[PDB]
């Protein structure tokens, strides 16, 4: 049932033709403050702006003939929707995207630019799931989970795979945590390339269901948390993702929005890169324990840079 | 008198130990709109945030023993000041930096972080040059020109050198233009690596003294131009830089602030990178003629990303 590093390896092969082997950035400013060597895997530079492109492409690249012709459908309010839309376009698969009537104009335009057929719903009614079921069952459309899927998580893991192949062994790896696709895929990669590398997942303190699950040994559900980390407002971990996280992740950490904001500002002012709030979870945690990272080689996964410009300007002004 | 490609080559060797071999980014979105292949040399990822680090280091690496011990002094309101400060620190040379009393806090903090000794003056009186002469002559401090210097321009040219070495021949190269250090150094590199590459300098339309000089065959002086391109408000080209530009640059183009703003927004929203207004001059021009760049391989020099956060947020909200 559970994917292994071999699936991450095969995913690298499947996506090689379309995915970006994103650059790894370093900062003399960061290295100084940490008294270590930090390596940033920039998935904000990934096709469509987030790491999710990897898992979306890996999953769509394996649908059967009937599904390819019928098409796919998404209703997620996060990066998965655009990851699926772009992946579908690249693979010649029709894609319908359910979005709120008040969705950011730039996001709607981007989705249409990805060939996605936009279907809107009223945000106040929040009829998303109902609509997704009705449309998908009637039209034979396939819905790919944003994280709880073997193909999706294996694909997300290729970012870490690339990081290790480029910089070599790492003593610590920090990864953003929502549903757990990125973390589980990254853990598979880390355990293979660096058995002794400490792997950490990071959640917003207001939504530490992943942390609670890790402690309890069972998946814990919570009400949608209020936090600026819009991509980590997950209510619970996935079955596949948690099964791997529980076995291959060393610990789950949490950071405050205040910390996410300082990190977002730092990325902009010191490293000159645009990172969405949720994509700051990993570095914020690392900074929070820079004292325990002495002279180690540390990997930071920058998950994405898809933040509404107005919102970005807002946080930068905080 | 004039530096040649050989000086750019030797500069690469002098700075190799401290400068960043900045990454080259590409965009499927840009390639589509241009119907070509575009390559972005990211000097916003250079040490200190701008390409000037290269020329500063090349010049300071060649001062005599007396000058190294006495120190250097800068009074420029742009990136050159911090380029000199950081380069001086790295080379064990004292550096005094003259800044306005109302200089951006983050910039002052950065300069101090670079070991620079800050000296302030009143912005309304603008006593900068007077002070710089008085202090430098009394203390035996050396002042390095921000662009009109053989060592400075040769160093700036290594960015283009690196671009050509990484991506190979290019049909067109777009470079930002202020005093002409970047352009002249880049032209030297371009003529060597790609004899047939069209080299273009780009200025803000309000300050097209470089364009006028190129047309006239003589250096033209203008009053400080009003434009958001704070790093290209130069009143005239340098003697060394113009001498090279006149012989090795194909043409000088100009863009409006409106175009710079759209470019700054695009870099943030589509490529996820922070670029200061002046650093958008090169891409803005390229877009303005994307139709004449058919199926070519085009190089874009992103000169820097040092823009006050508040100012950056402001432009992003436009
Ligand atoms: C989806 C997403 C996450 C969370 O990833 P999961 O696999 O759900 O844990 C984090 N950051 C960004 C930018 C995302 O798009
Ligand atoms: C200094 C500077 C320029 C202009 O370079 P010159 O060598 O004066 O032509 C352009 N962009 C940035 C970001 C700069 O710092
Ligand atoms: Mg959570
Ligand atoms: Mg000018």
Image: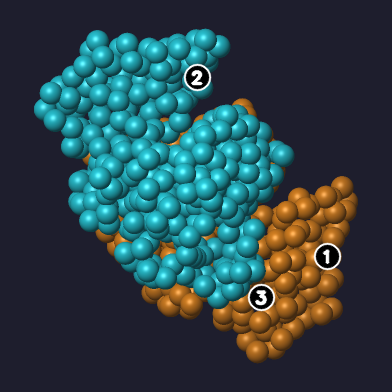
Chain colours: A cyan, B orange
Residue at horizontal 84 percent and vertical 78 percent from the top:
B138
Q: State the SS at label 3.
A: helix
Whether B291 is drawn above or below B208: the answer is above
Left/right placement of residue A311 relative to residue A129 reads right
Vertical comparison of B237 with A143: above or below: below
Reading the image, the residue beneath label 3 is B89
Q: Horizontal placement of B221 versus B12: left or right?
A: right
Front-lying residue, B234 or A99? A99
Q: Quadrant of the C terminus of chain B?
A: top right
Residue A252, percent from left and from top: 53, 53
The span from disc 3 to disc 1 (Cα, nearest Å) is 17 Å
**Residue with the mark numbered 1:** B119
Helix, strand or loop status at disc 1: strand
Residue positioned 32% across, 11% down in the render: A134
**In the rendered image, is residue A125 in sight?**
yes
| Residue A257 or residue A265, whichever sits in front | A257
Pointer 2 and pointer 1: residues touching (CB < 8 Å)? no
> Spatial distance from mark 2 to mark 3, Cα to Cα?
49 Å
Q: Residues within 10 Å of mark 1 (few under 14, many from 20)?
A: some
Residue found at the far left of this picture? A65
Q: Are marks 2 and 1 on the same chain?
A: no
Q: Nearer the observer, disc 3 or disc 1?
A: 3
Q: Residue at x 83, y 50 (%)?
A: B102
The chain containing the residue under callout 3 comes to: B
Looking at the rendered structure, the secondary structure element under dot 2 is: loop
Q: Which residue is mark 2?
A: A103
Query: Does the CB distance between marks 2 and 3 fall below 8 Å?
Result: no
**Res A230 label:** none
């Amino acid at each position: 049932v559970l994917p292994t590093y071999d699936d991450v390896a095969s995913a690298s092969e499947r996506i090689k033709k379309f995915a970006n082997k994103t650059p790894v950035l370093t900062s003399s400013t960061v290295n100084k403050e940490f008294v270590a060597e930090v390596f940033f895997k920039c998935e904000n530079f990934q096709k469509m702006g987030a790491f999710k492109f990897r898992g979306a492409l890996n999953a769509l690249s394996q649908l059967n003939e009937a599904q390819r012709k019928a098409g796919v459908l998404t209703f997620s309010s996060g990066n998965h929707a655009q990851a699926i839309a772009l992946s579908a376009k690249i693979l010649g698969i029709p894609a319908k995207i359910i979005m709120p009537l008040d969705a950011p104009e730039a996001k709607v335009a981007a989705t249409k630019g990805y060939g996605g057929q936009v279907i809107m719903y009223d945000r106040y009614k929040d009829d998303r799931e109902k609509m997704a079921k009705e449309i998908s069952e009637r039209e034979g459309l396939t819905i790919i989970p944003p994280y709880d899927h073997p193909h999706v998580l294996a694909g997300q893991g290729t970012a870490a795979k690339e990081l290790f192949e480029e910089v070599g062994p790492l003593d610590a790896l920090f990864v953003c945590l929502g549903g757990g696709g990125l973390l589980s895929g990254s853990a598979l990669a880390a355990r293979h390339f660096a058995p002794n590398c400490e792997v950490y997942g990071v959640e917003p303190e207001a939504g530490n269901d992943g942390q609670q699950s890790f402690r309890k040994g069972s998946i814990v559900h919570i009400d949608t948390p209020k936090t600026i980390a819009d991509g980590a407002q997950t209510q619970h971990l996935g079955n596949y993702t948690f099964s791997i996280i529980k076995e291959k992740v060393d610990d789950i950490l949490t950071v405050s929005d205040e910390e996410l904001i300082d990190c977002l500002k730092f990325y902009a002012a010191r490293m000159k890169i645009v990172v969405e709030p949720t994509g700051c979870l990993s570095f914020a945690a690392a900074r929070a324990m820079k004292e325990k990272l002495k002279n180690k080689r540390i990997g930071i996964i920058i998950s994405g840079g898809n933040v509404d410009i107005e919102r970005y300007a807002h946080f930068l002004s905080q």
